[PDB]
Length: 27
Length: 25
Length: 24
Image (tube, rainbow over all chains, first blue to last red; front, side, top):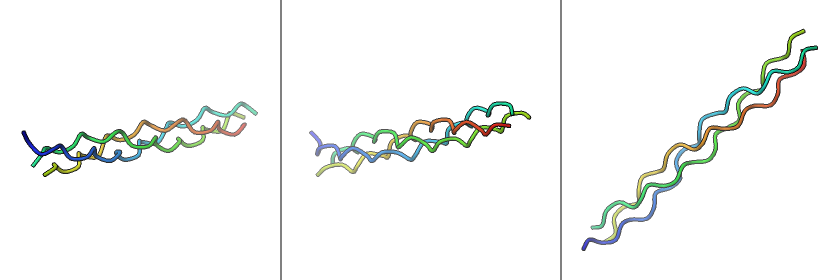
């Protein structure tokens, strides 16, 4: 058999920004 | 040599979105 | 000998919505 597999890779990049929040209420 | 290890997990959550729009007058 | 580290993972989840907007 081969050498062992290498270690697990690192976490990926940050996710994308979220959407805008809800609109504010009417004045 | 062995193979590459498994892929890593997903990264951190993304940043929050921007504030929502102002409400109507 | 061991293999190399695996690749970096996927991009993370999307972030949460932003805060509510201001009153008009």
